[PDB]
Amino acid sequence: MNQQGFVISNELRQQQSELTSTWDLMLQTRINLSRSAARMMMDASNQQSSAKTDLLQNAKTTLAQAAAHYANFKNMTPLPAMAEASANVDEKYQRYQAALAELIQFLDNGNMDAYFAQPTQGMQNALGEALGNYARVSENLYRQTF
Amino acid sequence: MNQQGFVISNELRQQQSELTSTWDLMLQTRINLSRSAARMMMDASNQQSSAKTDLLQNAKTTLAQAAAHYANFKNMTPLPAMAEASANVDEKYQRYQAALAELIQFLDNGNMDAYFAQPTQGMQNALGEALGNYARVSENLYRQTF
């Protein structure tokens, strides 16, 4: 229907929002984990809450928040035009969320070797790429509506 | 003019694009610097290009790319409705771009102490916040046009 433009617009609006929230968060989680891993050597110092003192904790919350965000995005059924794009993103998200979930495990148990061996970058890049696509396909939509 | 909707739309389209590119990049630069700082201790190993071996180099390019992006955004005069928002973002960007430029200096000269003392987070958060505003004000625009 004519007036339905807004309901199908705000939907494609929130799909983009929380999606950019997820990325912003996993991107902030990887930096938090590095601040913990970096300081888990010569410049340790802090004894109160050893290991999980400050940034490790902040990196558990940031992933938790990115999980909460995406959970909504996945809750919304993708438009027929965006089905193949949404899936590509979902898959790429699975790998990277997992990668970070394991980096948190690694930092919890002092597994530095494991930490620095996982090729986290490729999985981050794989997700960004899928994101740029979804966005392209997504913006195109409105342009194919004005 | 009536048809001008597209020229004023695509403009507010690219302003948002390259702006999200900048953030994505500084967010990727801080993670690169941590990978370098983290490994600039027990798990060094690599002798080819010591210090500036891999991630330090990648972190110079990512900032360089984020600089290139924003340079465009700043090149575009802000709409009367977005002037006060664009400025708030500019300022907050100045602090954080600088913060990262110095973390690169720190990692180049082995200044680990300086590296872990700068309160990078507050400046990142200060920028994200200003970004959420600009976005709000920016999205509102089209909604105040449909």
Image (cartoon, coloured by chain):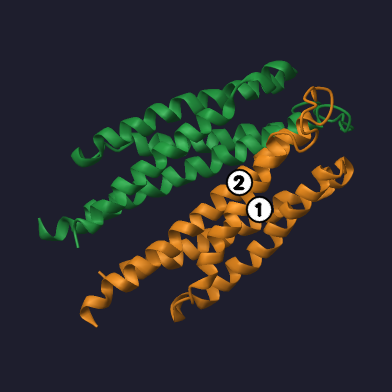
Chain colours: A orange, B green
**Residue A27 horizontal side relative to residue B91, left or right:** right
Where residue A134 sits in the image (x, y, percent)? 50, 65
Residue placed furthest toward the left: B1
Quarter of the image where the N terminus of chain A is located: bottom left
| Mark-to-mark CA distance, 1 and 2 | 8 Å
How packed is label 1: few (under 14 Cα within 10 Å), some, or many (20 or more)?
many
Q: Amino acid at mark 1?
A: Gln
Instruction: Compare marks 1 and 2 and give the one earlier in the sequence.
Output: 2
Q: Amino acid at mark 2?
A: Leu
**Quarter-of-image position of residue B43:** top right
Residue visible at 32% across and 68% down? A9
Residue visible at 34% across and 73% down? A8
Q: Nearer the viewer, residue B12 or B125?
A: B125
Secondary structure under tag 2 reads helix
**Labelled pair 1, 2 in contact (Cβ < 8 Å):** yes
Q: Is residue B20 visible?
A: yes
Residue visible at 59% across and 38% down? B62
Quarter of the image where the C terminus of chain A is located: bottom left
Q: Nearer the viewer, residue B95 or A52?
A: A52
Chain that bears disc 2: A
Where residue B6 sits in the image (x, y, percent)? 23, 58
Taking A38 as reference, is A45 above or below it? above
Chain that bears disc 1: A
Taking A16 as reference, is B128 above or below it? above
Q: Which mark is residue A124?
A: 1
Q: Are marks 1 and 2 on the same chain?
A: yes
Residue placed furthest toward the front: A48
Secondary structure under tag 1 reads helix
Q: Which mark is residue A27?
A: 2
Q: Which mark is residue A145?
A: none
Where residue B38 sits in the image (x, y, percent)? 78, 32
